[PDB]
Image: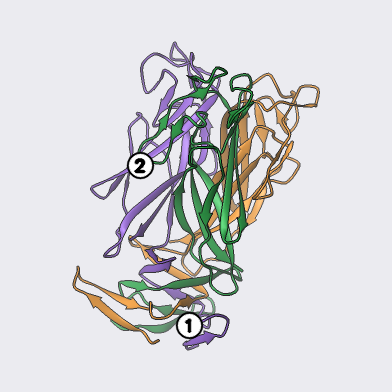
Chain colours: A green, B purple, C orange
Amino acid sequence: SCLSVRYDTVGNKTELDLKQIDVVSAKGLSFESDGKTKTPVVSTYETFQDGGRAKTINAIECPTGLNNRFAAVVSSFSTAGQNANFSSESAKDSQGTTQKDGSKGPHALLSGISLNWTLTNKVWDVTASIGIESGILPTSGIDSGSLLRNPKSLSFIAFQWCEN
Amino acid sequence: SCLSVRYDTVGNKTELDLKQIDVVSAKGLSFESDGKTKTPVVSTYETFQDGGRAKTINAIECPTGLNNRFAAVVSSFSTAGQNANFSSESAKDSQGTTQKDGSKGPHALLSGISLNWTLTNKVWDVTASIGIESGILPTSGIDSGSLLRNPKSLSFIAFQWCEN
Amino acid sequence: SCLSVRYDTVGNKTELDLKQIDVVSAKGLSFESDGKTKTPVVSTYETFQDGGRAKTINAIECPTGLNNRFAAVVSSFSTAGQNANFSSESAKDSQGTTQKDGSKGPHALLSGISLNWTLTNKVWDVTASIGIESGILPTSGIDSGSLLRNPKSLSFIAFQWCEN
């Protein structure tokens, strides 16, 4: 197979040709993007566990000189709050929104979703809330007022990478 | 240009320096992230075709030993259901929600979005539903009850990668 | 440490082993995915500035022969429109929806989110709108009718990469 450093006339930049080999297998990998050094983005499917508490996600190990980064993005969601299980990538259970007596009623209408994350001691602490129409939820509890706190009725993709 | 294997005192890890060359060009590529072997995430903009059926997406070819992975994430959405075309990245057509007579009325209010995916014979079968306020849609059809099935009024980014 | 080109019997493909070195450090990097040439996806957290105007994002520099690509995906959102600041990854300010007199009232209910992007002279021009229940907003302004234009009450992840 072999390999070599070629050069194209279009511009003034060199290139290391590895396309003769079918796969390049590395351990750690970094590359540059407009002067910044990055590692590849790595993705995980995430949900919150029962109980309305923050979701902890271990931070990836970064090469020397690079800092941990994180982004969470919405995949599926509903206004069911705790009354849900979104932990399967292929099916969702969404029962409905808790009513003032504690029963599961229809799904409420939605006003927003917040996803928040902070890095503490090589752990990302992720929190979320879903805002819903008022007048439905109990006065107190995980799902109360107009807010579904750290809801089960949410799946997000967590992206991590390292960057200078 | 040339290249070499350097070593930094910060820690106890080696490094293959290729930064003297402007571009490294590979065919297949894998790297490690906290002990797991991955290939780079690759992204495609996706919408459903007319008719309320599942969206099939071919699975990428994976190196030996690695398994196919997938994640879909929300980009744009509305409650128009079938009455939409979101297939352009630069503009959206969203006409409104089907009413009980079959006409296009105002956009209904939303209670959730589900995105689901399953791998079958090197094809990802993607399905989606948007939940809306009740009392608007016809009793039967693709958009019926409180659900917009496999809606046109949705764009998602499909991420694929391989992993052990 | 050293390195070499190995070959596995599973199939008929070669492999360049770099796993003896702890990190592979490149400048530009491209790889192939099912015949297409790509660069790694790179992610940035984004919000709109005050005033309801488009969000300009510089396009990354691409290797020779490759074209710029972009995808925006939803992270957090609400119906507050201009009455918000989502620019922190760890906390959100969302005050409420503008009412007909100009005051900040409760958050309105939502019918959709559009994220649009166009490439002009190595700049991505990103626009967004959030559709809300009618009868709430003033008749004119950035947030008017049933639309919140280029809203502050939105964070998105911008992904860029290059592709043939």
Report x, y in % for residue A116: 61, 46
Report x, y in % for residue B9: 56, 85
* Amino acid of disc 1: Thr
- The image shows residue A124, relative to residue C3, as above or below, that is above
Say whether marks 1 and 2 touch (CB < 8 Å): no
Q: Nearer the viewer, residue C108 or C72?
A: C108
Question: As drawn, is A106 to the left or to the right of B37?
Answer: right
The residue positioned 50% from the left and 69% from the top of the image is C63
Report x, y in % for residue C75: 57, 44
Quarter residue C34 falls in: bottom left
Check disc 1 and report its element: helix, strand or loop: strand
Residue C70 in sight in this render: no
Q: Which residue is mark 1?
A: B14
- The image shows residue B103, relative to residue B49, as above or below, that is above
Q: Which residue is mark 2?
A: B117
User: Which chain's residue wears label 1?
Assistant: B
